[PDB]
Amino acid sequence: ETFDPTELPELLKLYYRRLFPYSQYYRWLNYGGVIKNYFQHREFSFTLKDDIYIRYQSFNNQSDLEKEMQKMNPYKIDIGAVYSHRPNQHNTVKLGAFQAQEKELVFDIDMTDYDDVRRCCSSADICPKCWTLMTMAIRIIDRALKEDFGFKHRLWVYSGRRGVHCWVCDESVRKLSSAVRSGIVEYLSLVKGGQDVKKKVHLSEKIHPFIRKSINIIKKYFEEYALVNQDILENKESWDKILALVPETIHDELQQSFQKSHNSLQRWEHLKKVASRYQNNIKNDKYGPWLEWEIMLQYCFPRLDINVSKGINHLLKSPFSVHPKTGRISVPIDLQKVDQFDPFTVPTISFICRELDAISTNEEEKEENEAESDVKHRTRDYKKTSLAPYVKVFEHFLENLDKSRKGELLKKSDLQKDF
Amino acid sequence: LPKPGTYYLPWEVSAGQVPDGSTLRTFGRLCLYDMIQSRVTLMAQHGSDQHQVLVCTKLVEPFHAQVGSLYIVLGELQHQQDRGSVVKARVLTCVEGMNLPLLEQAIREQRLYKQERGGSQ
Amino acid sequence: GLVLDPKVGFYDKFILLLDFNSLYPSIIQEFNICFTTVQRVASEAQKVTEDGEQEQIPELPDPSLEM
Amino acid sequence: LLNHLSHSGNVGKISLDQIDLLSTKSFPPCMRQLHKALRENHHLRHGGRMQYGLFLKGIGLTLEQALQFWKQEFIKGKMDPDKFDKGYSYNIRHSFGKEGKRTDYTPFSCLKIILSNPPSQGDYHGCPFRHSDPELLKQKLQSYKISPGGISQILDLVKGTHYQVACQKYFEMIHNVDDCGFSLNHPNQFFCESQRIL
DNA sequence: TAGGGTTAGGGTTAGGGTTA
């Protein structure tokens, strides 16, 4: 059913009462307590009704967190960095000695940053055809992180409307400084330039191994999507803005070829033939020898933002949130089934509340006379809901992290000669 | 808001007669300032006995040190696994010339009055 | 109280000055301004909460109502 | 000796309607593009917004005048006044250090702006001498009636990565002065010298 | 015929929920 802003608060209260995975959330944040009070020194920033902004809300323990969540009923949940003192008592320490120490490396991808290139929708609209954009972006970034740097643990979260966030949560990464993160983001960024700049790539004859891997893994998706779905070379103004990306020496010839041609496939083939002919006939041209490659990267590569990762005290939306516009709950995305992730099929708050009502209806004749605490009741509650695959994926990631901790402690035991 | 700071003479806290995580305020005389590791070892005499308390200082830098002088420390106590008992400093001021016996008698009298008022309830 | 800003100029010839009599009583008499005859359901200028620069002035009470 | 080694923009109040003429006269290139975009679309993102606010604060604009200016230029952007009070004037109040931590902020320097975060699509902050196309830069210079010799000199300076010297040349051309006589380091210097000329 | 001047005097209220 259509989400209405005039009915959300009661559903939000019910969700915070029943379905919010407090146990797994605490288990992830606590990190096993290897470092004293590591979870106790985290900064939170809620957002209550009437768009009032508050921050610096620590939590002594999991039970206190549950009680405060039940009482407060906030809209957006965010995660900060770990400091040297409890954030709620930040005014009790001399100024300058209260500094951020560690936080998880994150990246953001904004779907709306492709308006000048995309034509499927307008502004804040989405289509199933354009989802391949963030799909291939996810594949590229995940492969680059997994291979080039070797970061072990990764957790992809769909924001809810147009974005997907990266939550790198390894051990040897949380201690990095700002300069190293800036270097990471610079190395992972290729689309460079402001509004005034048209061409987003200036590549020489030499090609980096990273660019080679990207272009190899990008061919299998560029053809179908670009040629058939979006049809970049459809209209006159389309190739009119296309030809601005190439030297003027063949502008008229390519325009005549497009006029002769009928569909975008023929125009793309003629562009490829002309480019190949020019490469064999290179004569004092400052342009790179990869016209086709550079145009595909310009219209196909993802775009990041250095500001969200350069800062160490910055804030970003926590998973399992509730977007106040569509009611879709932010859920993790499976790494091995990315191509089967339809954005429109993610369960919403209204649907999950009706599911809870039907679950109670079933409980009227299936589960009766139970003297259990709220823990087991809520466990079976979110087991019976539609979030079960998502929490299962979250639990599998947590199990992987726990196995990594077991391996690291066994390695420490081997080094320390304690058996 | 934090928890208040109750007084404690050095030898009681030296024997670990307080629960972990409590907030306490005590006194003593500095003996060594480990520069690199941000650790302070102050001492206080008791007849023929000398007691030692370890003080983390990570929250009051920069901080001048006066070797062989009295001090007042207020903070929270954490029972470490190997290091034992260390107090997390929040405020650390220096006082000199103040006689100990007046202070000790003062806390003794205050404790006695609190217990006396506690006899009615 | 509103100050008028008419055509600006200086005239040294004869100036004729007039003043109305009992403007507020005349307004009350003409439009039947009274507590028992005026309601407070509008959105004109004065009596609304701080939601923006718009508030409520009561409209003209119906002359056909009881005086 | 330690004291020796330890090292050792307040123009009077202005109106709210002369800003357009001063912009057409006194704004340096590193901010003229930002002003033009603000006057065209009546909307700007964070990177340009803090830069513009800091500059206007540093050239003698009061809290009330700046609030009125922002509310006017954003009403021209089809907003709601309640939403303005909740978000934008709310941010502006701490932009000048009225409340909150009240740590008053100095305007960004020319060097910092040139070496700041690179703008992306939907952003206009940053000096055009560093983050603009040569053809667009030439077109915008021609829109300011720059002599062809001055255009060639500006292009040569840009090629030499001497953005400050290009800004000096632009100042000299717009103000019809043969020599500026002062090294450019901060937009407040540019604005104060322009006001001195006026 | 015994002290001076003898006078009653300040006596309210102010607002969180914030970062470059």
Image: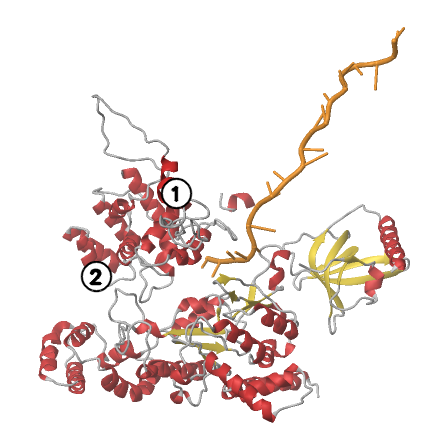
Colour logic: secondary structure
Q: Is mark 2 on a helix, strand or loop?
A: helix
In which quadrant of the rendered view does residue A255 lie?
bottom left
Residue D136's disc number: 2
Residue A43 in the figure: left or right of residue B54: left
- Up the image or down, D132 lies above or below D64; here it is below
> Which chain is home to disc 1?
D
For label 1, the crowd category at 10 Å Cα-Cα, with few meaning under 14, some 14 to 19 and many 20 or more, is few
Residue D9's disc number: 1
What is the three-letter code of the residue carrying label 1? Gly
Q: Are marks 1 and 2 in contact (CB under 8 Å)?
A: no
Decide which of tag 1 and tag 2 comes sooner along the chain: 1
Q: Quadrant of the N terminus of chain C?
A: top left
In which quadrant of the rendered view does residue A27 lie?
bottom right
> Which chain is home to disc 2?
D
Q: What element carries label 1?
A: loop
Query: Which x, y percent locates residue D21?
Result: 25, 45
Furthest toward the bottom, the residue is A366
Query: Same subunit under labels 1 and 2?
Result: yes
Picture mark count:
2
Closer to us: A264 or E13: E13
Query: Which x, y percent locates residue A80?
Result: 53, 68
- Up the image or down, D44 lies above or below A106; here it is above
Query: Which x, y percent locates residue C17?
Result: 28, 26
> Can residue A417 be seen at all in this image of the molecule?
yes
Residue B26's disc number: none
- Up the image or down, D162 lies above or below A197; here it is above
What is the three-letter code of the residue carrying label 2? Leu
